[PDB]
Amino acid sequence: YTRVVWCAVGPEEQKKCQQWSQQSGQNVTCATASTTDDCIVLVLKGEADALNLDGGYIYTAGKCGLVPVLAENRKSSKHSSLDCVLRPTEGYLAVAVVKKANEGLTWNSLKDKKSCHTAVDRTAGWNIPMGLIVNQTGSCAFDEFFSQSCAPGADPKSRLCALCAGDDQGLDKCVPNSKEKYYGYTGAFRCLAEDVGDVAFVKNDTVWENTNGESTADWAKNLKREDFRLLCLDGTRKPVTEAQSCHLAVAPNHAVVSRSDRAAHVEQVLLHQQALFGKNGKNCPDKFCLFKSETKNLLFNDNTECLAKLGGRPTYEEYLGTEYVTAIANLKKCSLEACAF
Ligand SMILES: *[C@@H]1O[C@H](CO)[C@@H](O[C@@H]2O[C@H](CO)[C@@H](O[C@@H]3O[C@H](CO)[C@@H](O[C@@H]4O[C@H](CO)[C@@H](O[C@@H]5O[C@H](CO)[C@@H](O[C@@H]6O[C@H](CO)[C@@H](O)[C@H](O)[C@@H]6O)[C@H](O)[C@@H]5O)[C@H](O)[C@@H]4O)[C@H](O)[C@@H]3O)[C@H](O)[C@H]2NC(C)=O)[C@H](O)[C@H]1NC(C)=O
Ligand SMILES: *[C@@H]1O[C@H](CO)[C@@H](O[C@@H]2O[C@H](CO)[C@@H](O[C@H]3O[C@H](CO[C@@H]4O[C@H](CO)[C@@H](O)[C@H](O)[C@@H]4O)[C@@H](O[C@@H]4O[C@H](CO)[C@@H](O)[C@H](O)[C@@H]4O)[C@H](O)[C@@H]3O)[C@H](O)[C@H]2NC(C)=O)[C@H](O)[C@H]1NC(C)=O
Ligand SMILES: *[C@@H]1O[C@H](CO)[C@@H](O[C@@H]2O[C@H](CO)[C@@H](O)[C@H](O)[C@H]2NC(C)=O)[C@H](O)[C@H]1NC(C)=O
Ligand SMILES: O[C@H]1[C@H](O)[C@@H](O)[C@H](O)[C@@H](O)[C@H]1O
Ligand SMILES: O[C@H]1[C@H](O)[C@@H](O)[C@H](O)[C@@H](O)[C@H]1O
Ligand SMILES: [Fe+3]
Ligand SMILES: [Zn+2]
Ligand SMILES: [Zn+2]
């Protein structure tokens, strides 16, 4: 066997990867980059093998020839008896979240408010909400819609980064990695929870995992679900229990990608790695758990039950679905058939 070189995005992922490398006995090793885009370039050069990507990034990687290998699979209810690895993925719900106390803020009065985004180019944090906003406003000036934002990956001197905080020292403001205080699902929800923004564009799971004591993190300790509302497209506000009827879209699960010529090798290694360090793995929680990182979703989402085989050997377009692909295509017209690298 050859080793698999995993690509870690930023210093916190690098630390988790190093631990996994040690525990795997160097069956997995680590390369590190500052952004997801740079990790994708590493994979293309053949300097790294794989990383787990949000749907929006799978689109970028796909244009450049990378293929989906295995998908994150979280808890379900349907397909009960079927093993996690073979169970179809269900997809997550992209939602827009506000404080209950911010009364009369609805989908239709979002203009000139403050926004919290997981990162530019990501499914729930960006592509879905901004795609809808462009369509509804007939304008590609989505950078003038919100008064101020935190959208990791945008220009640090623009309004889109105005609310981003950087790291401990206030360095790396708006970098699309976990060094940025408000990056990712948990970061964007924190941006709302601390009332830096009026709205966060996250997924349904984020609200549940960071309220009612599900998170012992300082800022999330006292957060109650009832203090939050979801914004529906029909102009209403619902309790966070109603996400099935009040979401902006269903997103395809985050998935491991690699170069096509390395796909089968990456697959084999990962299946074995999860038997050891996965949810009921030999060595988890005794030595190391691949799918834990204390609420920080490092390398993988913390709610990941397993990585699932795909079936139908999907291309990246099949994986993302024709609905989502055309949504992205239409939005990319603002800022068509190539590879950004
Ligand atoms: C937005 O995000 C949230 C966070 O991701 C989502 O909430 C999460 O939902 C999942 C399920 O989708 C939860 O997992 C469950 O958590 C339970 C409690 O911790 C766990 O323990 C039990 O598991 C049992 C087995 O499932 C459950 O017993 C039954 O299970 C079966 C189906 O498997 C059913 O059987 C029925 O029982 C009926 C009894 O009245 C009977 O009348 C019927 O005839 C039938 O026999 C039944 O459904 C029943 O539940 C038991 O209920 C417990 O759940 C378990 O592991 C389970 O998987 C997460 O815990 C939730 N996360 C959090 C933090 O709350 C939310 O779903 C999502 N929203 C949307 C719309 O997607
Ligand atoms: C922003 O605005 C953009 C412009 O309006 C939006 O893009 C448009 O999005 C539409 C929906 O994704 C595209 O239509 C495509 O899907 C159609 C429906 O597919 C079929 O639907 C029927 C009924 O539900 C099913 O029975 C069937 O199985 C298909 O799923 C397509 O119509 C059909 O396509 C099939 C292809 O196999 C064809 O055989 C049929 O004859 C029939 O024509 C259609 O072809 C499209 O693929 C629009 O094309 C698209 N517009 C543009 C400019 O591309 C965008 O979504 C908006 N953004 C957001 C975030 O919402
Ligand atoms: C590192 O990879 C190797 C190869 O998969 C593993 O070593 C053994 O592989 C052989 C042949 O495939 C199997 O018969 C054994 O099951 C493996 N050894 C054991 C004891 O399980 C090895 O498991 C990997 N090491 C770690 C820690 O991930
Ligand atoms: O596909 C994406 C997208 O086009 C972004 O606008 C660009 O900043 C990224 O580098 C690219 O990978
Ligand atoms: O249309 C289907 C669907 O998108 C599945 O998720 C994928 O696994 C299949 O390969 C594809 O044919
Ligand atoms: Fe996502
Ligand atoms: Zn829906
Ligand atoms: Zn196919």
Image: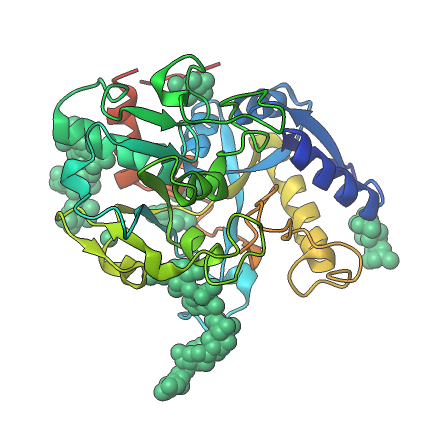
Residue nearer the viewer, 8 or 257? 8
Counting from the top left corner in percent of width and height, residue 34 is at 61, 22
Q: Regarding ligand 2, which quadrant of the image does it lie in?
A: top left
Looking at the image, residue 60 lies above or below residue 95: above
Relative to residue 83, is residue 45 drawn left or right?
Answer: right
* Residue 159 appears in view: yes
Residue drawn 79% across and 62% down? 286
Q: How many marks?
A: 0
* Residue 325 appears in view: no
Residue drawn 30% across and 46% down? 98
The quadrant holding residue 340 is top left
Relative to residue 319, is residue 229 drawn left or right?
Answer: left
Residue nearer the viewer, 264 or 61? 61
Residue drawn 83% across and 43% down? 22
What color scheme is it? rainbow
Counting from the top left corner in percent of width and height, residue 305 is at 56, 59
Residue drawn 45% across and 29% down? 62
Looking at the image, residue 290 lies above or below residue 61: below
Residue nearer the viewer, 34 or 283? 34
Counting from the top left corner in percent of width and height, residue 175 is at 52, 23
Question: Which quadrant does the N terminus fall into?
Answer: top right
Counting from the top left corner in percent of width and height, residue 183 is at 49, 34
